[PDB]
Image (cartoon, rainbow, N blue to C red):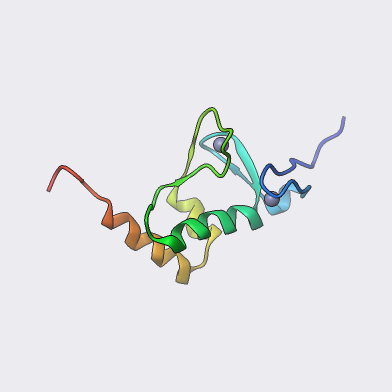
Length: 94
Ligand SMILES: [Zn+2]
Ligand SMILES: [Zn+2]
């Protein structure tokens, strides 16, 4: 049977499982490249830390854990997200 390529719903491009990342939240796979630009573009902003799914048509609307991002982006970048997390912590409990 045919297998190997998982395809992408972001850049509409085909890529090997080698350069892809399967989200263990919404069984959503995407090419590192995209996922990288996605989580990055978001963090870079500095308004929201939670890295939702890069898919607008996600019935599960999963999120991207920290572990994923950590690797996805580089230390220099991660930091930006790391600080963003704290900013939004215990909005009720002090
Ligand atoms: Zn892609
Ligand atoms: Zn998803």
